[PDB]
Image (cartoon, rainbow, N blue to C red):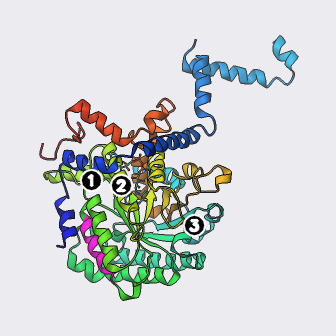
Amino acid sequence: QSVSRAAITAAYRRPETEAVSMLLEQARLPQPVAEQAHKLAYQLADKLRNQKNASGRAGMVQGLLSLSSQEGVALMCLAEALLRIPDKATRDALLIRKGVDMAMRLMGEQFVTGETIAEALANARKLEEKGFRYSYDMLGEAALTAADAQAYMVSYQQAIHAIGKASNGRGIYEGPGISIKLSALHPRYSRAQYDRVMEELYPRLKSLTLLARQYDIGINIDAEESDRLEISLDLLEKLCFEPELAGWNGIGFVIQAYQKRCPLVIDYLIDLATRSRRRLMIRLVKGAYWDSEIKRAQMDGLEGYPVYTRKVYTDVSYLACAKKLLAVPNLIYPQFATHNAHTLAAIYQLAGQNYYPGQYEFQCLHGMGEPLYEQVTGKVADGKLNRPCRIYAPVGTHETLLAYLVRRLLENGANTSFVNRIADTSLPLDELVADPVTAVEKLAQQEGQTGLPHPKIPLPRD
Ligand SMILES: Cc1cc2nc3c(=O)[nH]c(=O)nc-3n(C[C@H](O)[C@H](O)[C@H](O)COP(=O)(O)OP(=O)(O)OC[C@H]3O[C@@H](n4cnc5c(N)ncnc54)[C@H](O)[C@@H]3O)c2cc1C
């Protein structure tokens, strides 16, 4: 393997104390930057939470209470009835499968942009008028048969034609793009071998990428489970050297900060952009498959996890990786995917003075990020930050929704998730937007060393 490929492999399941200790001084915000990130994060999270005055209203409720909850309700029901007395004088003087299917569809609706690419493309004008951008995700993954993969191929091809016509020359930055999953383009990808992936999957990836280039829209390769990282790099490496793609910078690639390999993957990507003479569109995410990654490692009984076991470590990893990406704007267009107010504010500060549109963009999932990003994308005059956000827009029917929805349920329902915590009016804003580096050092001082694994998540062999 090349030097940078070797380093990736060696870091696969690096001990957490060692990986976190390494990332820490790379992720640490210089003092004035930390202060500004904190102030901005606090302000974003304050507006997000208290837009319709949720905390003030909760603090009138508690302030009334000397009664019980359900009691105070009884009173309000009465006070409401009294306020419906028109005249104040009078007032004063006085099966299992189908249950799961329905619940999925009902909870999943909010995360879906449209049933078909045409409906999706139509629902996007409203936010596009405001400076938002889109990346369309034709739902459907883990193709089991040759036929399934073929259908996904056809669906992607048709989406590119529709998106590309809608883009009408706006280009890879200002115009919409598409996101694809490699698992959709090859039967039984989860266990597919190198030779068959190259022989069958690659011609599909190349074909779609060339079509995306013809319309000049971005084409992003989503990141999936950790044991597919390697083959996805081999596929990316070959793609970047196609003569037909020379001089074109619309190839996009996701990297997952929850993996120990992430910074090493960045070193590889930097070298690849250099050798293949292009700017790569790189989406930095934390990661969508954490629960399954943990479970898989525990069943396979290997020496360690390929992901961090404490959420704060992933946050620290994201910040370190963000700095690495921002240091090479000639080689990488970073796309910072997050719904976390601190993370956003930190990136905003880390990106430095003198923003220009092609420096970087934020990204968010449809149904999750719009309220936060409504403070971000737009004009300074309107009280926004004037930073563009690209909305990830799932497209498809109920038959294609299950796996995506489950990942959204895990993301939204986890007590460690920012989106879950901000919805807790009890949890103070300062804790919500607490600096992850400082949080890691707190743990270290309490525990006896830096980057210990989650106490409840022993090594697979233990
Ligand atoms: C536009 C967009 C595209 C994305 N594309 C992909 C993709 O192609 N592939 C992919 O894997 N993910 C992808 N993601 C990420 C995933 O879908 C989540 O949205 C993202 O991880 C949430 O991060 P955060 O900064 O919003 O939230 P936060 O609440 O800040 O962070 C939550 C994340 O922390 C991580 N985490 C949770 N618990 C632990 C723990 N105990 N130990 C270590 N880490 C933990 C998980 O990654 C979790 O998602 C994408 C996200 C966005 C917004």
Q: Nearer the viewer, residue 312 or 420?
A: 312
Side (left or right) of 164 relative to 237: right
Q: Which residues are magenta?
A: 228-241
Can you tell me whether the CB of the residue at mark 2 lies under 8 Å from the nearest atom of ligand 1?
yes
The answer to whether residue 240 is magenta is yes
- Residue in the picture at 47% in, 68% down: 138
User: In the image, residue 428 lies at what x, y percent?
Assistant: 48, 31
Q: Amino acid at mark 3?
A: Ala
Q: Of the residues under marks 3 and 1, which one precedes in the sequence?
A: 3
Relative height, residue 292 to residue 282 (above, below): above
Q: Is the distance from the Cβ of mark 3 to the nearest ligand 1 atom less than 8 Å?
A: no
Q: Are marks 1 and 2 in contact (CB under 8 Å)?
A: yes
Q: CA distance from mark 1 to mark 2?
A: 10 Å
Q: Secondary structure at mark 1?
A: helix
Which residue does the image show at 54% across and 65% down from the upper left? 357
In this rendering, the label closer to the viewer, 1 or 2: 2
Give the number of the disc on residue 12: none
Q: Position of residue 141 (x, y in %)?
A: 37, 66
Q: From the top left corner, tell me how far across and down residue 429 is, in percent.
A: 49, 34
Residue bearing mark 1: 293
Asked whether 165 or 446 is in front, the reply is 446
Percent x, y for residue 380? 64, 53
Mark 1: amino acid: Glu
Q: Nearer the viewer, residue 418 or 113?
A: 418
Query: Label 2 belongs to which residue?
Result: 287
Location of mark 3 (residue): 120
- The quadrant in which residue 414 appears is top left
Whichever of labels 3 and 2 marks the residue nearer the N terminus, that label is 3
| Residue 429 visible (yes or no) | yes
Indicate the amino acid at tag 2. Answer: Gly
- Element under label 2? loop
